[PDB]
Image (cartoon, rainbow, N blue to C red):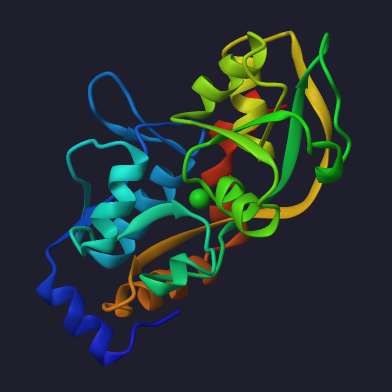
Amino acid sequence: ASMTPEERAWLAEHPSIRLGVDTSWPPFEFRDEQGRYQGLAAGYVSLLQERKGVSLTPVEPKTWTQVLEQAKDGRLDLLPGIMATPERQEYLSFTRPYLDFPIIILARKNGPMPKRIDELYGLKVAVVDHYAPHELLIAQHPDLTLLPLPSVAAALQALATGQADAFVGDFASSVWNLRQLKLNGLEISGETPYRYQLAMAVPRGQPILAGIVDKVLADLSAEEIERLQAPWVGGLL
Ligand SMILES: [Cl-]
């Protein structure tokens, strides 16, 4: 729970921490039309800011692909909502995950309905570009045919309009956007063996902040965790 002496000294040197966030990933991370960072991960960030006493501020908006390049080039200090992959461990260090959801398969009601990953071979499978579902599939199922799209909404719209035959993504952002875009033509068709493990990451060359954040996240009360999720359970259920 407590910071060590070196962690306190590091916080002194970083009055501001540069955050890399997705502009269009509700309910986890989005920038409203005023440009303000919102979402479930933004709530965790606001709590970290209170605890750490330093300013955690998103930098200028970029595509998520660009954000990951910025973190490779050490042009960012913290990514608040990202899943670990083996490839990412080469340039990022991660907290332990603070939220965890299944990775599921969405279909059109008038279209094909794959039950598992093995019923995806032979279909055009939409995924959000450079999120972990995409990277897991490339590494573990190279012969699938994927359609990476820039946002969950773009991907669900591709599925809903027939441009994709299925979509693979995490449970929470898939259901949130299905209902908020009112795509009453889609449904959940199946399961994968994969979990979406939402964590925060820092450049692997500067691991102290992931240690600091991990300690704060692990020390959260049951009460605090409930309040952090309460604005967002509504449009999942
Ligand atoms: Cl990710």
Residue toward you, 213 or 227:
213
Kindly identify the residue that appears in the image at 59 percent across and 37 percent down: 230
Kindly identify the residue that appears in the image at 39 percent across and 53 percent down: 80
- Up-down: is 12 above or below 117? below
- The answer to which quarter of the image holds residue 11 is bottom left
Residue toward you, 79 or 44:
79
Residue 75 image offset from top left, x and y in percent: 18, 59
- The answer to which quarter of the image holds residue 30 is top left
Residue 175 image offset from top left, x and y in percent: 67, 27
- Up-down: is 142 above or below 236? below
Quick check: 178 left or right of 102? left
Residue 209 image offset from top left, x and y in percent: 31, 73
Kindly identify the residue that appears in the image at 30 percent across and 57 percent down: 50
Kindly identify the residue that appears in the image at 74 percent across and 9 percent down: 185
Quick check: 166 left or right of 41? right
- The answer to which quarter of the image holds residue 2 is bottom left
Q: In what quadrant of the picture does the C terminus appear?
A: top right
Q: How many marks?
A: 0
Quick check: 68 left or right of 117? left
Does residue 86 appear in the picture of this structure?
yes
Q: Residue furthest bottom?
A: 5
- Up-down: is 73 above or below 32? below
Q: In what quadrant of the picture does the N terminus appear?
A: bottom left
Quick check: 126 left or right of 129? right
Residue 129 image offset from top left, x and y in percent: 48, 38
Does residue 234 appear in the picture of this structure?
no
